[PDB]
Image (cartoon, rainbow over all chains, first blue to last red; front, top):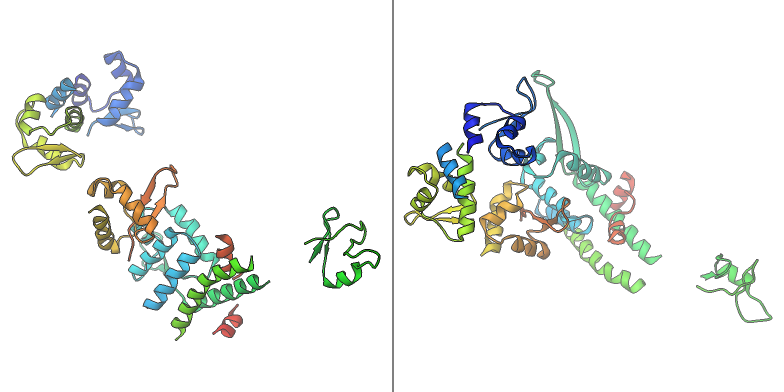
Length: 64
Length: 168
Length: 143
């Protein structure tokens, strides 16, 4: 949920920025992000995930 | 063209698997396609469509006209026209079935020498001392399916009857 | 960020093992009562929207496959999983139609346990006997 609020706050971010926040291995961060976010490998923002309700998603995460 | 389609389905049953039969039926559904139309129509890829196209090219089953769409938007258009040619398919099937029958219609060997002899060689290889066919150099003894081919030929006979019905 | 809510709700539908009302989802998933949660269920094929009130369930087969092939008469390919979703547990019916050699099935060139089913438009010794060597004059002699 926190990472998603970052995604509305940042259209581009990194597994490093996410691992720094979540203190979890980038491999785990890369799995879930594949679901919400998509990767852009070209341009200035290359190697960074971009997105495609947030409160409903957070409550769904709390339920699961 | 129902009889020709039935002959093509019989050829698909005899020659190759079901995917090729389905591709031929898909071409039969739609009048004309150009080089990309099977790919839009099918879930197979173009490279694999290419192995199948090479397999069709190996035989006379179908025909290709190679045409460009002239209008000068970029590189124009490579359109290929795949239209079945009935005479070539009829000729190839007849040659194959007759050749198959000839193969179905179509002896002495020595165990140690691994040589091979025939009837004329039988007159030569006969010895008066013993009763036997003896090898030439090694003087070794000489030693030496159709019904099963006939049953498989029963399958060939229905195809021949279908060809006769298509002819008349 | 509406993509995640559907999965946490659906996997919850798998965990609960029973359908959940939209209000029961919206209360349990703590969301404002909305059409989008239902609309994601109406959109998602892994969840069934029930015309009676709210209900959301997780998500004749040979005849359905034959009718699909007949409608497919213009279409030269179909997806295996989509046909199974249209007629739950249709993979077996697809394989049976294959063995019958009518709606025939195509064995997976990717994982040899899987099989694709396809829509029907409707031995090498044997094959070489049926092919052999493959000209115009013998055809004319044949004609």
